[PDB]
Image (spheres, rainbow, N blue to C red):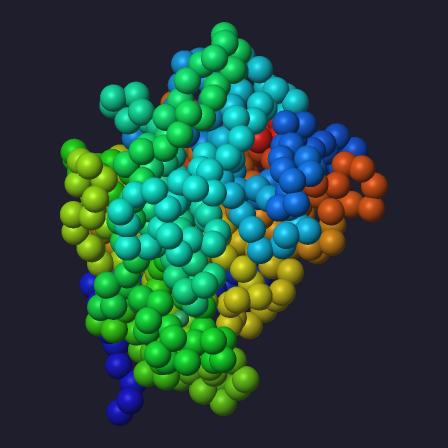
Length: 448
Ligand SMILES: [Ca+2]
């Protein structure tokens, strides 16, 4: 029959595990901590110039810290460094990477100083690159402190003028200290594209267009590159979509048992509901993946590898790829919107962080807490303490990881700008994770 089973040698976020989350999620083991609304403040240094030229308060969104190769928070001349997407909502479609810095001793949100944008509007047109001159927006990624002590950035080149073309891009961020308490962005070098999809392993923007993606409601992604090191090799783990040969999108995917899990009755019943319903196209187009590529020492592409995990039929969008080694095991994390998912019981308000454990970097990834659920955030987008872009930050010692996120902060009264959310702790024990109760940290805190 049309029924088949194709794993493609890779792990999968299965429908059976996802349908079990609703009846599991209502627990303080998974619930994102309730944040105290009165103590929420804007980032004081989040000042910037709008597209008009006037100085205004910026909305600060997705943020990532400068990391050591193993994932721990780096120390740069006595400073912790955070890269963050920021911009003016009055110019809705614009995100630029800003550099925030804080002395290691300081703790408050007021202590975070702003070095400004990493790139000038001119920087993208300087080097000889096949993609950079088409960039409309700067999107998320990662930052690593090299063995040479250089600030190495990885981010996403987004092109709105090229049908939403997303390219994994790198640059060395040249720094200086004008005084004893100030970091300055001097400029950038080694600014170049690395990877934008191959077609077979990861979907290109051309295939998106060619299948009529702009009308069908397809979501093309190739973003959020996260740097990691293992056995002397250098990798980027990133949000992507499957190519033609590792489980492509389309109707046939709904017949693939590997994406369902569970028993045959579950497969037959879940498939039947999916083929009949209004979620048929949505599930068919859903082919999210967490991809991995190896890099050369100069940070160019070395090898395009098969994905670590896919979310075929489940969702087309698995965001903020995160990976780190702990207790000899490899942990993989992803943020997911319930509004993008096709699962019964999961709704528009549900926002998740999912987690997976493997014995090797490229081995079989098994779901944490049985289902993959690690964090559940279901606060209305209108709430002041709404949080998004949850990211697990590994620590030097202890079993706890620090969770960072941005708080939209859209209240009717001041303060009212998207800011650093208060951080919190999550305990990791084997294939089990739990939120540490009543340990709410300072806004944008990286370490404990
Ligand atoms: Ca897709």
